[PDB]
Image (tube, rainbow, N blue to C red; front, top):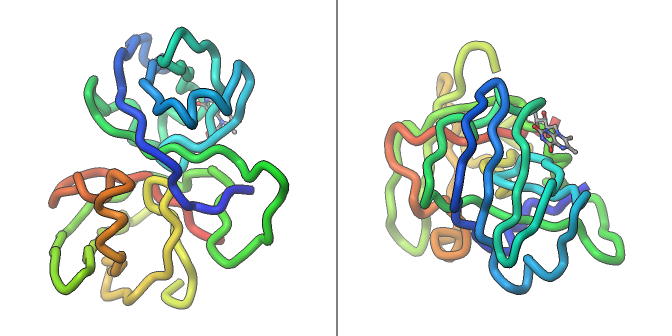
Length: 180
Ligand SMILES: Cc1nc2c(=O)[nH]c(=O)nc-2n(C[C@H](O)[C@H](O)[C@H](O)CO)c1C
């Protein structure tokens, strides 16, 4: 179990397209890089993945099992991914605890920045509640409202800074974890 609190951003450095599989090499920030090793299972954009290789600051993952239910297949070199390593000495399982099991891909309907808030409206596709949390790209937060097929999450603006939520646009695909 993870908290859905993103600890840093990685930047995709390389992608190997073999694609019912892809290998992503992601540049990690020093503090995260030094806590991981081959075999580390951690969350990348909310998705549980295993470190295959580390060379200097580039941490590699093979996306295979996850390839059909996540955004990785369509990511590009330079893109920013959310990173979270499991709690070191345990945690109290809330609430919005994440498993890293991504239920599927959804799409940003609308984004508005106003009043110290990042308001994010996500359209949930047919084949994929409002008192629950939801994980989006590994960010766990309470749902604000649901209207039709669209879920409204009202994030504090600081999450714009510390996660890739602040790069999202109308039409951006995201990894959704429902809980549960
Ligand atoms: C531990 C783990 N490692 C990987 C991995 O290295 N590569 C991969 O593609 N999938 C892994 N998985 C499974 C994914 O977390 C799971 O397939 C997705 O969350 C489903 O959307 C898991 C659970």
